Amino acid sequence: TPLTFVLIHGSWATAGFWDETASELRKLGHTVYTPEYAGHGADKNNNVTHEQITKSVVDYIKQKDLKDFILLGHSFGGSVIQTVSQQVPDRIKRIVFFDAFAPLDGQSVADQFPAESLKSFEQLRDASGNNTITLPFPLFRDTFVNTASLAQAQAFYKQAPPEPATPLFEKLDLKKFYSLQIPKSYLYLTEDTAIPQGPYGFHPTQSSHLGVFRFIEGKGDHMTTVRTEPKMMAELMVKAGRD
Amino acid sequence: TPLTFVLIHGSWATAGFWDETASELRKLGHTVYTPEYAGHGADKNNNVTHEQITKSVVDYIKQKDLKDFILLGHSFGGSVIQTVSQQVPDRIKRIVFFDAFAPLDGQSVADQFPAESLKSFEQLRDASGNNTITLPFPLFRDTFVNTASLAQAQAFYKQAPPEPATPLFEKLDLKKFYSLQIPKSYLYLTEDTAIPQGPYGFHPTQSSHLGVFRFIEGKGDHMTTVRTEPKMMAELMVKAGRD
Amino acid sequence: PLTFVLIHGSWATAGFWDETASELRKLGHTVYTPEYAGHGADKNNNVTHEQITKSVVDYIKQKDLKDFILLGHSFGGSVIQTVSQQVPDRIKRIVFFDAFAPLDGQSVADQFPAESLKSFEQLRDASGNNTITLPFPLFRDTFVNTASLAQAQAFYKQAPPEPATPLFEKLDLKKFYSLQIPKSYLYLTEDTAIPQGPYGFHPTQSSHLGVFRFIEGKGDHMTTVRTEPKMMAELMVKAGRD
C-alpha cells in the first residue's frame, strides 16, 4: 500500500543526498519529500542552532500540511527526527532511524562519540575559525564511503559540505520524544563506520537507545550505498517504514 | 550424507512452527521429527513445568528409539535440548542451538533477558491471572517478525499461542549438560531481535555460553524466515548439523 | 592495476593464497605470495618473529618492490606490522584480513582468551619439538566451520604444525603505531578462529588500528580463500584500492 516518506539528511550532506534513493522509492509508488533545513544546502548560517533546524523542518511539514507519514533520519538527522517528532507527533505514522544517532535525554550528538572522535571534532570546529567542521577527505574516504571507489568517493565528497558545529554539541531535552508511543525502526548497514563499530557503533549501541524498535539490516556504508544501490535502499526503507 | 533431525520449538509456538522447513529438509533426503511437548499444542496445562516438558521429549525419543540424531532447538527450545541431552546423551550426534537460549547452570530462560524485558514478562504473567504470557502484537510484530509484512505478521501472530509461564522462570540444573562431550553448533540469523541485540543478544552472548561450537550465520528473524524461506533454512540447518 | 604482497598466517604456507592470488591476477593485479622463515620448505621449529620478519623484508628488498599493498591473514597481521615498520617508504596501504593486530609490547598469544592461551602453551609443551598441532575437532568447527567434513579433512592436511616461538614473543610496534600509511581491515562474518565476542577479530582486533577502512564479507578463517576465491579477490581490491 502507498507510503509517504519525509527524509531528513544528516551532517556533511544536503537534501540531494536522497536524489537516487528518493527516485527509486517514487518508482515503487511512494510519495517522498526531501526537505532542506537551516544552515544546510543553500542556507548559509554557520551559527545555526538545533532549534532553528527543527523549526525549518516543522515549518516545511506544516506548510504542506503532511499527515500519516514515515519520518526517516540519517546520521545527525536522527536527532532532528527526535526533536521534530516532539512538535508534530500527531502527524507521524512511524519514525525510522537509518544509521542515525539517537541521543538520550540531556545528551548531544557529540556525546555519542568515543573520546578520540569527540576530540577530533572539537579540533576541526576550532581549526575553522568560523564554527564549522570540514571532514578531512582521507577520513571521509575510509570511514564514510569505505565501500566506494576513489572516483565515487571524490564525487560524493563534492556533495559533503562543511557542517555548522553548534547543533552537534547542544544538549537536547528529549523527555517528550522518549514518552511518545509512535513506533520506531532502525535501518542499519553493516559496513557503516562513520562512528567506529564497537561499543559506540550505530548498532547495537545507538539503536538500543530506542528501546523497542523494528530492526532492518542491509549491506552498505554511511554515504556510498544511497547513491550506488538506490533500488535496494528504497526496498529496505519500505521494510523499515511499512506497517 | 542423510541426517536425522529432532526439532524442538520454543515458546509462543507449537510443533507446526517447523511445517515448511521440515518439509524442505525431507526433500533433501533427511529424516525429521517435530515432537509436541507438555503444555503446548493441544496439551492444556498452564501449570506445566520444565521437568514435565523435558520428560515428554525424552519419552518421545525413547518410544521411537531414536538415535544418532541432530537435536535442534529454537528459542526456549534451547533450554529443552540442554535438559533432554542430560538424560539421553548416548543418542545424540550433535546439538544445534538455532536462535536459542543456552542458560548456564543455575539460571532460567527469563534470566537471559535485559532487566526491562524480564520485568515486562513478569508483568504479563501476573496480568494473565492464569500463569500465561501473551505477547502483545506490537512487540511481536516489531521484534519477533520484524522482516515480515503486516499481513504475514498477523498470520504468524494467530499461530503464537499464550505461553505457560513456569518453565521460563525455573532455575535449571545444567551441570551434566556442561560436562557433555557432544559437538555443538549455533545457527544465528542476523535480524533476530526476539531478545534485543547487544550485551544480552543471541550471538555472541547466548552462543558464547556453549564454549567451543560451530557457528553458522544466515539472514532472517525469529519467526518469519522458517515460514517464508524454508529451503534456505533447511540448507542452513544441514550446514549446522552435518559432520 | 595494484600490486599486492600477501602474508599467510599460522598452520599455513604461501600456498594458502594459490586460488585467491590466481583470481587477483585475472583482475589485472600483480600478486606476490612469499614464503617466510620456518614455514613451507624451511624446517625450523625454533624460528623467531625477527627471523620471519627479516625473511619478508629481504624478499621485498631483493625484488625492489614498491608502492604495494601489504596484506596479512591471521598471525600474518603481526608480520605486516613488523615488516611495515622496516620498509614504510615502499608501502601504499596495509590490509589486515581476519588478522591479529597486537598493541605495542604484546604478542599474538596475548590476543587469545585465557583458556586458549593455556591450551596453546600445553600443545607447545606436549609436542616435545616447540610446535603446535591444532586438534582436528577444534580446527573443523572453529577454523573451517563453513566447510564440509571432506573439505575440512583436505584443508587440515594442508595445515602443518606451527613453530611456537613467534606466537608468544612480545613485539616492539612503536614505529608501526606512529605510521601514517593507511590501514584497512577485511573481516569475514563467520570467522571464529578466535571466538566472536570480546576477543573477536572485529571489532576487537580491528579497533587496535585506530582509523581504518572496514570491508566486510561472508566466510570463515580458512575455507573461503579456497572455495570463493573470486569473491575474496574482489574484497581484497575493495580493501586495498586507493
Image (cartoon, coloured by chain):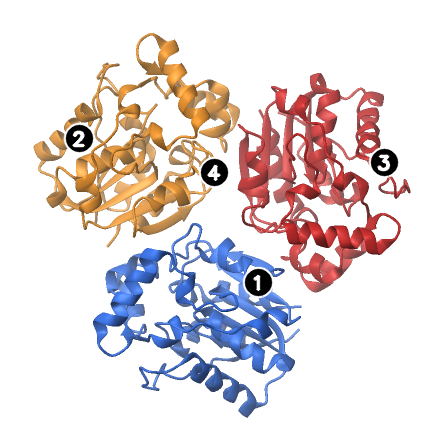
Chain colours: A blue, B red, C orange
SS for callout 1: loop
Occupied quadrant, residue B63: top right
Q: Amino acid at mark 3?
A: Ala
Left or right relative to C161: residue B35: right
Residue C230 visible at all: no
Task: Say which quadrant the C terminus of chain B sits in.
Answer: top right
* Separation of residues labelled 3 and 4 (CA atoms): 35 Å
- The reply to whether label 1 and label 3 mark residues of one chain is no
* Separation of residues labelled 2 and 4 (CA atoms): 30 Å
Residue in the picture at 71% in, 40% down: B76
Where residue C168 appears, as percent x and y from the top left, is 30, 24
The crowd level at tag 3 (other Cα within 10 Å; few <14, some 14-19, many 20+) is many
- The reply to whether label 4 and label 1 mark residues of one chain is no
**Chain at tag 2:** C
- Residue where numbered disc 2 is placed: C56
Where residue B191 appears, as percent x and y from the top left, is 58, 51
- Residue where numbered disc 4 is placed: C196
SS for callout 3: loop
Q: Amino acid at mark 4?
A: Gln
Q: Are marks 2 and 1 in contact (CB under 8 Å)?
A: no
Residue in the picture at 46% in, 69% down: A74
- Residue where numbered disc 1 is placed: A210
